[PDB]
Length: 119
Image 1: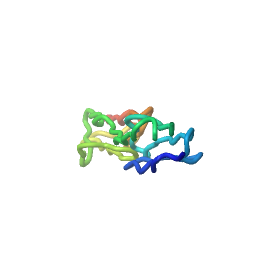
Image 2: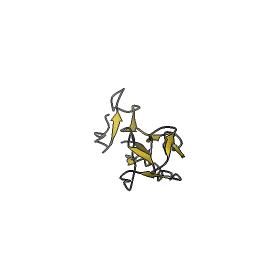
Image 3: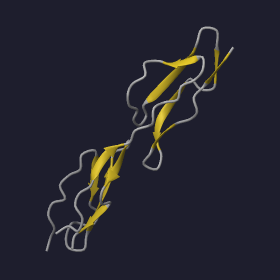
């Protein structure tokens, strides 16, 4: 009375604490920087729910600043990825030099607010 092999989830992982026999449940998760999409767990009643997906969390485009630019700005930003600011000729930077893309509640949000350039 045993269930089919869970299989596998790209960029995520199937957890199996109590076997896969009748009554056992498998849980699902994803690698940091990704958020699960679909059933968060399947129960061996043949499994109850089908396998979910792991989609990558992205941070919205970084903010721009006055009298300041972003060095080599890419298209997308994932977990741990960072953006770096530099003040223009004649200005001095206040605040932090660079912000990092984070993952909050399966939503990519930037570490903090962009720095400021003063004269």
